[PDB]
Image (cartoon, coloured by chain):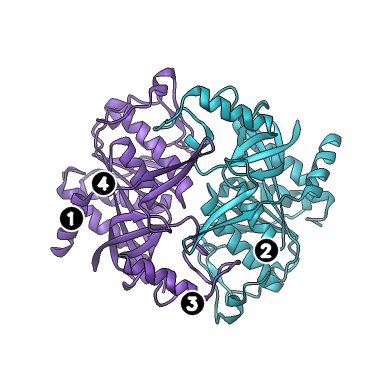
Chain colours: A cyan, B purple
Amino acid sequence: IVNSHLSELDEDVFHHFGFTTKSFDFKEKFGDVKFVCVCGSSGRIHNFAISMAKLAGLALPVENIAGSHARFVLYKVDHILFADHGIGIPSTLILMHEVTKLLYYAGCKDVLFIRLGTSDGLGVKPGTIVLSDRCVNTKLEPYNELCILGKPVRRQTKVDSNAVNELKKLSENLSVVVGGTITANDFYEELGRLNGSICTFSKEEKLAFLQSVYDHGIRNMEMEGAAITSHCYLTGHRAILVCVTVVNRLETDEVDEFKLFEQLPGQLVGEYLKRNNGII
Amino acid sequence: QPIVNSHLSELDEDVFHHFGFTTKSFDFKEKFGDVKFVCVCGSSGRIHNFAISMAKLAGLALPVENIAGSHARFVLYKVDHILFADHGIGIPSTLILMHEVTKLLYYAGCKDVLFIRLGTSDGLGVKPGTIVLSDRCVNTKLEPYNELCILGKPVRRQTKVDSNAVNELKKLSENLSVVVGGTITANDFYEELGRLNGSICTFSKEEKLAFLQSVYDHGIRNMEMEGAAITSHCYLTGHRAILVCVTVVNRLETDESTDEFKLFEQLPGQLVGEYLKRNNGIIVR
């Protein structure tokens, strides 16, 4: 589906990237992109871009394509774009809008979006990589909910099951678990944490909620999945979540090794990108 | 009297993961006990500069120390009775800040603290560069609520702004344009704010205008993405909140000079700074 309104613009400003459609030719600069790698922070995604560059044999430093003062960073190593989305669905939706618009202008078709994040684990020990076989909200519905012009809109989530299949098969020759993922808007109360500044439920209700979602296949929880997987589906691209778990929420709320866990998703996806020509 | 989360007493040590410190990091009573203001905005650089401007005003020697961990998600500064932090973009990011900052205030025994958001925003029927003092914070249906889904169950939390602080800021500006009006909080910069140049648009330019005109006639003068989170969380934790946002675009005209934008961003700080100087936010030495 195409936004007809874009073709009417004399110039289109990427407010959060720091450039416009008069900055450069998008086809020439981005036309070969087939993958988009994203995580929460600029630092981590830049480190991964650098890591991927070394794997491809790129000597020169990986340079920010985005404006220096812009909200998000943007790196490119061969056929891969790297960017940060911050914390939460709204921040992520901004990135998704501007990155998919970028892909549209560049003529990129059927691009795989990969989120390499961290997450709360359910019934798995910390350090476990969860490959999301589905992304659902806190009601375990595979939908991202929006209020557009004051009207309720539900947009269903979808994961590239083929990519999950590949990543899981690949991981065996290189622990990795395939399971469901909850996306929430509140790190504390909506994720059943007891140590927020506000708590309107008991431990019993918290555990009943966390056990039920586990029983219904959920293995991890985070705050951006529903946005990425729903937005990609609608704009003609693909999406997967590769997140390491940093805590078993069926056991506790609170959390060197943390930095080590963060490296794990990149180690898996990097090998995937190598064997599926994200790099030359 | 503020409601206390009893579960916090069950913890021997509490970790502020997004600030990168714990309850053993400082003596919270001695370190934060005199905090009566918390200033927040979207970026670490902007709020750092504002903290620096307040320190200069207070006659305090630079630099302003980031109390937060070096690799933490958020920054945290203190100048006399004011804390400074960034909240990033959107309600989820902001809610995390609110939880950890209000917990900090609790451990430090701080009561009735005033949260001030110094942001930029979409304008409605006002020229770019206009400071909107929010007298009302609502969602995209123009209801004064932040909606949540707690353990799968729908929750609506009422929003509230400090009218007295708003009134004081208004009168202060007269002796220093500033408009008092409604504020919409949305969860999406593009479609939910009625922008036509997203990657997805399921509405016409006619429907767009109707939506924005409607909210304008209902008193809304600006739109941003964090308001309902701040004002509802403060209400529940026994604190106060206001929004002081400069508008950068009049959405009733268009959806689209970097120098004057930098000038615009300075405006909320200039107003708020004067308020803090006269209301025991800083001590002038």
Protein chain holding label 2: A
Quarter occupied by the N terminus of chain B: top left
Q: Quadrant of the C terminus of chain B?
A: top left
Could you say which is closer to the camera, residue A215 or residue B112?
A: A215
Determine the CA span between mark 1 and mark 3: 36 Å
Q: Earlier in the sequence, mark 1 or mark 3?
A: 1
Do the residues at pointers 1 and 3 share their chain? yes
**Mark nearer the N terminus (4 vs 1):** 4
Q: Quadrant of residue B78?
A: top left
Q: Which residue is mark 1?
A: B167
User: Where is residue A116 drawn, in percent x and y?
Assistant: 66, 45
Pointers 3 and 2 within a single chain: no
User: Exactly how many numbered labels are in the figure?
Assistant: 4
Does residue A167 show up? Answer: yes
Q: Of circles 3 and 4, which is in front?
A: 3
Kind of residue sitting beneath label 4: Ala
- Where, by quadrant of the figure, is residue B253 drawn? bottom left
Dot label at residue B206:
3
| Displayed quadrant of residue A176 | top right
- Where disc 4 sits, the SS reads helix
- Kind of residue indicated by mark 1: Asn
The residue indicated by pointer 2 is A235
**CA gap, disc 2 to disc 4?**
48 Å
In-image side of B44 versus B220 (left or right): right
